[PDB]
Image (cartoon, rainbow over all chains, first blue to last red):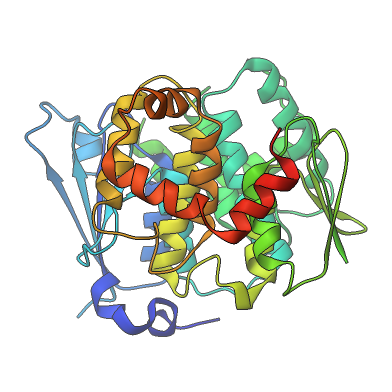
Length: 204
Length: 167
């Protein structure tokens, strides 16, 4: 796997420090999980702040956390989770699915075109179908997941990917439908990981 | 040969624009049909438009549709969602189109300085958005979006896709 430097490239320096704006009424569990994953792998300086946009953030949210990455979470009254970078030639990045993809990419694991796209496809299913979705659509998503998870331990293969992080996390924050067997197995395999159950209990 | 079946009744313009831009780089067939299916290999298909775009951009590396670095790739992911979620709704269009306008104020193409999946996705989505067509009709389109939209529209690939698929 690729080192952090070559992953970010020329501006490793620019991107080493990450800022995320999140709404306390809608904390992005997927990012919390990914923060935990990053900390296991990298030396990470983390910080929480509270924008004047909001008042009375609960404590767990407030206490939710020579380095390699800087990682600042700001509670704010934003309509959508948003990541900003020091380079501001670029646009702010909106949507936890997109931020999660970037963060997961920091681990430098290589994927061919098919597998990388399959991973992206699962993140979109989480964001575009599951999260704001119908009950009926949710059952269809479950069927599709159930089929994939009958063929491999994780959504996109033999390794954990951002597909798993995002889809598991979204599933926790919507709460109904019968959970099929492969999905149940996968759910407990996810929750068995410290980064996952740790972040989840934070949101209590 | 990769093969893309399309919903002929409602053509995925974004995907067809991507095909038009990668077709000299990778061999692709487009077939008439009633749904969108990119047939990659025997056990491998993609049926959602954004996955179809991503796969084409990934396999046609010389076309440069997914940007040239991680930050650009990320920005392109941002715009692919923006079109799928904000620009695909008619609720809140004014704020959405204004946001697009502001991002375009200092840019010629959405990401970097060349055509990317972000332009293809946002342009196609805009073109099929009724609120956009209404703003154009009423001469109320925001300046930067109008400028960017017209520039792409005039390009050869876009004209070609339009001739082959516009009703």
